[PDB]
Amino acid sequence: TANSHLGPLQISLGRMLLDILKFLFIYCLVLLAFANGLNQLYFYYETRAIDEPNNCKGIRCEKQNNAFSTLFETLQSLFWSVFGLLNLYVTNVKARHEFTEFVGATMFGTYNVISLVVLLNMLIAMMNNSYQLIADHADIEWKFARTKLWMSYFDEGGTLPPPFNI
Amino acid sequence: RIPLQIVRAETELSAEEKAFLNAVEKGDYATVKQALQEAEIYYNVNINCMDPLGRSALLIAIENENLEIMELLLNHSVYVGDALLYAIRKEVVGAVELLLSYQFSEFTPDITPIMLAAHTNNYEIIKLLVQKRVTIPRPHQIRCNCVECVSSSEVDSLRHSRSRLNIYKALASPSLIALSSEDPILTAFRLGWELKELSKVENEFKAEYEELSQQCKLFAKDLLDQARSSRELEIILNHRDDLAKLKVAIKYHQKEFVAQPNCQQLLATLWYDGFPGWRRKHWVVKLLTCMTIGFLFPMLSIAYLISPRSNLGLFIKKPFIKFICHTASYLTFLFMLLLASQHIVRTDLHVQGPPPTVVEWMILPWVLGFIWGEIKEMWDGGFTEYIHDWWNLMDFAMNSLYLATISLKIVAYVKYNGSRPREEWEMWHPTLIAEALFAISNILSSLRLISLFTANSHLGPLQISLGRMLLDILKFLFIYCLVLLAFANGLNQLYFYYETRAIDEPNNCKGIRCEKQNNAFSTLFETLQSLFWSVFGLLNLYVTNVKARHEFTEFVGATMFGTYNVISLVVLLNMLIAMMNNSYQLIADHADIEWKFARTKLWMSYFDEGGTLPPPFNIIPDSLIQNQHYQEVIRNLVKRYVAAMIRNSKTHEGLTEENFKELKQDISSFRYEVL
Amino acid sequence: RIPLQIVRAETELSAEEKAFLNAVEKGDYATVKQALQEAEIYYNVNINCMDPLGRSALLIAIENENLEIMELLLNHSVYVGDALLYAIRKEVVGAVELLLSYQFSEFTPDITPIMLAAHTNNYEIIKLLVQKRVTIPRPHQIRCNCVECVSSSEVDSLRHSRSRLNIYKALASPSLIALSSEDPILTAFRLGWELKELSKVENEFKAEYEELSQQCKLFAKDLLDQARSSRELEIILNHRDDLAKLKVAIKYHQKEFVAQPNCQQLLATLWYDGFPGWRRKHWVVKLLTCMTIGFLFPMLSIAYLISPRSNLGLFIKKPFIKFICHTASYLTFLFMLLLASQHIVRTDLHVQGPPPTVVEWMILPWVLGFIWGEIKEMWDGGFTEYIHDWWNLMDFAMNSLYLATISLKIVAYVKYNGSRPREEWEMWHPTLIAEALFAISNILSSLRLISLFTANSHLGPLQISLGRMLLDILKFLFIYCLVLLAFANGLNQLYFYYETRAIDEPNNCKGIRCEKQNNAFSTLFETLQSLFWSVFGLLNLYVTNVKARHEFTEFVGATMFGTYNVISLVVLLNMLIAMMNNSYQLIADHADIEWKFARTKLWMSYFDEGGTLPPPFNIIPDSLIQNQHYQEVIRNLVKRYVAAMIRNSKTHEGLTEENFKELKQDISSFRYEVL
Amino acid sequence: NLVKRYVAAMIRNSKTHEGLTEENFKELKQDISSFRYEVL
Amino acid sequence: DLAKLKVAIKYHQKEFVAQPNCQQLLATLWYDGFPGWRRKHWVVKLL
Ligand SMILES: CC(C)CCC[C@@H](C)[C@H]1CC[C@H]2[C@@H]3CC=C4C[C@@H](OC(=O)CCC(=O)O)CC[C@]4(C)[C@H]3CC[C@]12C
Ligand SMILES: CC(C)CCC[C@@H](C)[C@H]1CC[C@H]2[C@@H]3CC=C4C[C@@H](OC(=O)CCC(=O)O)CC[C@]4(C)[C@H]3CC[C@]12C
Ligand SMILES: CC(C)CCC[C@@H](C)[C@H]1CC[C@H]2[C@@H]3CC=C4C[C@@H](OC(=O)CCC(=O)O)CC[C@]4(C)[C@H]3CC[C@]12C
Ligand SMILES: [Ca+2]
Ligand SMILES: [Ca+2]
Ligand SMILES: [Zn+2]
Ligand SMILES: [Zn+2]
């Protein structure tokens, strides 16, 4: 805030943070719904770490497995699928249950569409709308913030820096 | 180098006619008199002479708003046809009264003086005309096949449409409505609805009908803002042709009427029945009261069942308490659904037909209550209204899935008796199908919780805006689907010659859901799935390679895939983003009105006494005086609105013109007195 | 329940003073006379009485623009102080002439009549004042340490700043400039430059100085638009204090002056020297002429070297031909660079110090020509201007890389003699370093081709807009770098305990550029690289796992990585997109002016006769009469501009006030004549 | 001082075309009526 | 010492605080030991 070029930008970003927090609620509700559904579908096919290669279990292994066996793991998998770090073979069970595998794949695809095609674009649109209004009064807010920052060094209390103030 | 001439020459009048027109325009009470005498005697002047710009002497006098010359000409029997319309358009009460006291035109031949006055919206001239027992034609139904309508549409469609539009524009006049209607609010509601419905049948003249409907809605609202007392507001809102007028306004989509601050205060007072000074409390104590009232939902309900007249039994009849209890019940149902898929309560995954567990036994009554409530609401309240909600579709799908799950479980329990390894079950085992349907219904039931966002001041408008953008998302889906189908057809045609069996693949896995993806374009279904999954980057690049060394075919397939990727990810998504931004820009203006309309609709569903108990517990087995009061209040509101609009009509241009005319009249009078 | 009173009471005047003020306001040539007589004799009235709203009788008369009372009061010796300023502000020439004929204020005590007239921009009053030999103070340099400036800034900074702003606002008046300057265009250029430079030193009053500079630029442009002949335009543009005035305008950043249509036509006529009717031809034939002229670039240059006076040798002296030849030469150089890295011309990749190949031998003269041209341009044309281009930086980097490559090749050839397998060479082999530098310089030289886009009507504005957004991209880079450093520090601190040697890893590969990524967070450099590459999704999720079973540490690392991913990819990029949109919205308005300024700057570099030959071939070894003409044209332009502005000054409010005052005067005269 | 300056500035800003036109029209009407009465 | 300015800050008077005359006074107080700070070049200020 002490700089003439970065201060207004920082104020604007801090002003948009609240609306980011607003979208977080809807995203969390959608995530919880789909996690509940996927865990309910897939909890019958849990496997122990002994039978997996390298004795590794979860989605942080080189060969991802047991992605939807527990609610916590399902939440983590659905979070990491936002950035594309979950592979497509995690929807396959060891047995040949093609109906179950297809239903799980359709659930995953619907979640991907809803999360990555709709919600993010709506977030971008309302970010643009918020910034349009915020950009008008950037100077006044930045100068108010800089005045508040300056006034904290006028008084004579706490003159010494923390290494020397004890 | 070509000269300019006059092609459509106008037949000029003689010097006598030019002098007469000049004298009439300038103003000479004696020169015009002697000119009329000369026209009478020697016929030197035509009494019906016309300006080349279609402006007779009477029209010149009318535009000069001097009444002496007009009265003299009327006494001299000049052609007076189509002059009352000019007087009305100029909005001169004295001249209108004068003509009412007894070729080329600027008005279409279907326009009447009353219709023209209504188009102008001048209360003084409309009242003067209506005082003489005038009438206005009323048009036929929107979809009418009568011979007269068919013949009129078959002879002159332009004339027919113009006449209909003129009649509706006259009927939609606020001053005419206030003067001639006994229920102006109801008339405005119905007229706005009819104009809105007509705008989509006459698609060519859509904007005119839209503006007329907006005018009617604005008139109704502005009439509502003239209430000065809670008693007057209650008289207006409770008038039955308990809040009958508010229900009618909701039915007719009067969002600005419903979202007015005086109505919202009354609705909030009704909503917070048992919490006087609710907005006085702190958010922390309000939150804690919410939690405590929520936890006591099993009680307050048994109390209502065993003693409705008791002090405890009358608590659940309040709307806010009822809403909190229903929300707590739904949250409990969702918590049990969460408990269903855990290790604590469900074990022994090896039985073919399993008896229901304790969690499923607990779940069943909630499902029965949901189905019973849906059926009861659909019966009592209107069948055609039940489908115009877009949430009842989700309710229907969820309940159908639950019913199918229960039926499949019963069928499996009846048919199968024993145990068998799950790995050797068939593809279409009833237990597997029931599990899949249960999971899908769980997803839907969890997603239902969105509709409770409209009750909050921060999430409601956002939810309304997203629901408004969904339609344009649906619009883009069509183009995307067509492009996807085209490219899938091409890729499948290219690659269908190189299909391989699952035996020769590693792990005996075939498709793109294997660890090593293969046969991505061997069938149309698989090609569609692959092209769908390539949108998110989950398809690898080696799927375009065939086992043989056909480099031309592999390159053509890779180029097809690259062109599809470019078109889908570089063009269509960015266009979607752009039009999302454009839609949100317009949507953000009216978010408050739409959110308040939605919240009013949500609140009004808890006012009635039907369906008080939540689903778990709901399966256990004078007029004349009111008319006079309404008429008095309507009189007061109309008088106040007319006075306010008249005082608002004072404008600089009108005041300057009036002062100039008055100064000219006084100067002329003083000059005449001096002379 | 507290009463309202008057706290800052005003000392009222007596009934005599109130009556005198009422008579003065109403207007009574005799009543005011007898009141002044009474004040003279009995002292019943104060001649210096003041309205409670600081409005003396003279001020009332001035606001009433009646001169008889003012003349009588002046004859009666009333306090006349600070009345000329009110007359000037009201802009009444008759009253201004009257006062020029011989406490509380609304004006700051530093304001002079000439400064106030200049603030008003009234030509008639400014001329009247300047006719009486008035002066205006001139301020000190922008950065001045003289004692008088230091003392003034140390006593009253508010007064000092207000006085400086008032002086500059007076000096920036178009009417004052036109009246008192002999070179209004040059004066406007210099004043706009000074105000623009001052706006960033007085950062508090930035907008005022910006508006003053914009006013000066607008005045200069509008003066230019008053030319009626090509001879007048050439006289204006070629005036030397060959296009000296245009070069000065370019130096002072006068974009609206340069982009005016009359100037652009002259520049285009100069640019298309050898193609009369170039815009008459079809785009196909123009394109074919471009290709043929491009292919003949080796000729037209040898012809210019061996016979400058010949018909063939004079062709390359035209600007468009010179531009085409330079472009063709650069394209040939780039084609040879492309040929350098092919299988046809380069073989035997096993020699330590290799002699230069034929392609490198051909490449060397182009590099020598580029360096020689850069040095020659930097010497001849100004050293400080050479750095304000932002393309000369790319030129310098590219030529430095080429020089380093040549030096390293020579050093390697001298030092090494023999052959050795490339797999056992050291890390810092001179041949390897030279190859890397050559590749980087190839990238830079290929990227240089962007600067030719400004010559096209479709790509130029787009290139200007992108170059305008680059600065705000640079602004976001800082915040991104800080966040990246914070998270890299945290992750390296968490994970530095689990480093492993390359021996124990498969294939003896260590880092994230291996097929199995490992040691992603073992060092700070590797952590920075991993966090950079995770922006594009090229880092796998198993890099957060340690070889031991430390689940708490692995979970903490995964949560750190997830938080970084959310912050970087969900928040910062979307904010960047939003502010990109906001910047482009404002940039898109003035794209044409900026593009035409850039194209003019590009065109003007080919007009001079220095550096005619392309780099491959450029290493082979009266004043008084002009002043009178300019003065005459300036007289004509100033007269036309003043007349146009005066005719534009006719406004409805002014005309209405003038007509009202004239009618009042005539009515009063007629009433007096009757009486 | 500040209140006096602010009030004077706002009063001088209150001068508007509509108000000035209405005032001039009323004053002209009054003067015309006075002249007519004097003549009569 | 700037009691009224502190009250204005407490009451969120952003337009009052950001006025140019107040900002000049605040800058004068802020640059106590560097008279003519804005006169210097950015390089020497940085050093
Ligand atoms: C992106 C990387 C390089 C960050 C490295 C961390 C630090 C070296 C940076 C981070 C934030 C920087 C600060 C950001 C802003 C300012 C205010 C700045 O004050 C002004 O610019 C005063 C003049 C004006 O108002 O323009 C003085 C440097 C300082 C403290 C900077 C000092 C260096 C800091 C601490
Ligand atoms: C994102 C995760 C935590 C969702 C978890 C599911 C439930 C715990 C949430 C989802 C939606 C929530 C509801 C959303 C909105 C409201 C309205 C709210 O009413 C008000 O805010 C009234 C006062 C006002 O108008 O501001 C009362 C809580 C309630 C029912 C919430 C109760 C808790 C619910 C059911
Ligand atoms: C995208 C690929 C094909 C680039 C290949 C590199 C070159 C073949 C291109 C890159 C930029 C091009 C230049 C961009 C713009 C111009 C200006 C252009 O001039 C006009 O258009 C003048 C008429 C007008 O003002 O519209 C003449 C061609 C030229 C030099 C182009 C010549 C061909 C160049 C060097
Ligand atoms: Ca329902
Ligand atoms: Ca250069
Ligand atoms: Zn009909
Ligand atoms: Zn000085």
Image (spheres, coloured by chain):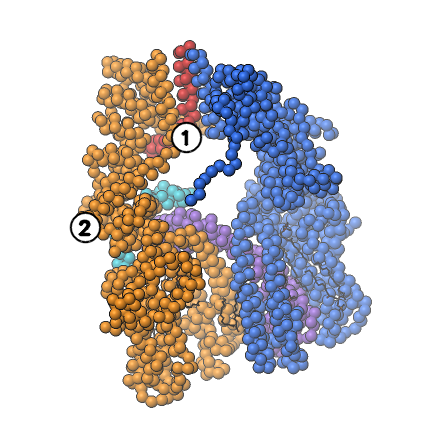
Chain colours: A purple, B blue, C orange, D red, E cyan
Identify whether C178 is placed above or below B18.
below
Q: Is mark 2 within 8 Å of ligand 5?
A: no
Kindly identify which numbered label has been placed on residue C126: none
Name the residue rendered at 73%, 62% in the picture. Answer: B360
Name the residue rendered at 45%, 17% in the picture. Answer: B668
Q: In the displayed image of the protein, which residue is found farthest to the top?
A: D40
Q: Say what amino acid the circle numbered 1 marks.
A: His
State which chain disc 2 sits on: C
Figure disc tally: 2
Q: CA distance from mark 1 to mark 2?
A: 54 Å
Name the residue rendered at 58%, 56% in the picture. Answer: A26
Quick one: B534 or C402, which is closer to the camera?
C402
Toward which corner of the image does residue B216 lie, by quadrant?
Answer: top right
Residue identified by numbered label 2: C623
Q: Secondary structure at mark 1?
A: helix
Quadrant containing the C terminus of chain B in the rendered view:
top left
Marks 1 and 2 share the same chain: no
Q: Secondary structure at mark 2?
A: loop
Which of discs 1 and 2 lies nearer the camera? The answer is 2
Toward which corner of the image does residue C591 lie, by quadrant?
Answer: bottom left
Q: Position of residue B327 (x, y in %)?
A: 65, 51
State which chain disc 1 sits on: D
Residue identified by numbered label 1: D17
Q: Say what amino acid the circle numbered 2 marks.
A: Ser
Q: Can residue B230 be spotted in the picture?
A: no
Around disc 2, counting alpha carbons within 10 Å, would you say few (fewer than 14), some (14 to 19), or many (20 or more)?
Answer: few
Identify whether C362 is placed above or below B340.
below
Around disc 1, counting alpha carbons within 10 Å, would you say few (fewer than 14), some (14 to 19), or many (20 or more)?
Answer: some
Quick one: A108 or C469, which is closer to the camera?
C469
Quick one: E23 or C186, which is closer to the camera?
C186
Q: Can residue B672 be spotted in the picture?
A: yes
Q: Determine whether, in the image, residue A151 is placed left or right of residue C529.
A: left
